[PDB]
Image (cartoon, rainbow over all chains, first blue to last red; front, top):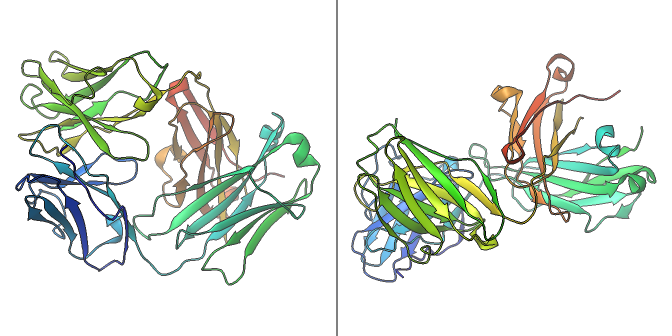
Length: 213
Length: 213
């Protein structure tokens, strides 16, 4: 109290489209609503103060709307760089409160990932542990499947994954997966492979290496 | 030149206290308020309170009262926020922000990461990933706590770079990947060095990445 509520938690749009982001103030706050843009690993950036008032330096395509309770953030013609999370804020009554955020995704033509596999360093092997890393580079959409196989044995539960934020220029994603094994386990097998499934690939792609080759 | 520079990342034992700092510049520190905002991991913004450095008058959000404490230091142009009897739930990024006139904030600090854990700090290990286009990178493994900064060639190489978000291992340590795509013919000409900095353990490491054999 007061509660700001923005409601699509996530939104996927095409560049050039018009985007409307809603914010429901659960109490009449007149034109005392504020909009912020926060991009990955960044502090918030004020887009619109007071419901619909301009902010210097902010691109003209951004605009605000609404009064009392229901509010709207609008992007005229959306650009790839508008990717990120959008917060609204109570600017009328303390305690100051923020909406939960709407994350904006930018659509693009389907792009298949570039796949690269990396063997463990001898430097790590000495420490008794072996990490094998599979890189999926610049793909769209985000949905991708990474499968680790060791001597055609499917691996499960011994790998961790991590996707990047959507690129601000080409709207692609990149993924990194690490298969971790003990030194003993690693040297008792030969063929290490990561299998990648993606909408941009007509058939699954496999990159591999034979240990010690 | 309005600049807000916040203190580095923190690791805090539960129940203990930490005093975060916000230094102001580019304006006359005396004149405008300074607010503090918390963002818990993968979540939204929650307001904490404000303080007028002109005299020292403060009002807080009051679920953060038996928790937060705000002070200023005009002689050094700096605001502080002491966090008391910390819980693992208090783990978050803490932003400071300068009002100009009302409840909206056009100026933010970069944020300060605070990790609440009984665990000790451990520096990472940096392992080479090593490969028309080639991919190479660094595996920054087994460190605590977040964050780690990673750059390539002292910042001179930014194109094609992807630094992935760290993953939390079963061991209780973080592991991070940072890669860059380069032409394979440059692997003989150009040197490639990932610059890894983990300030919670004061660890700076420069790792040159090479093909083997």
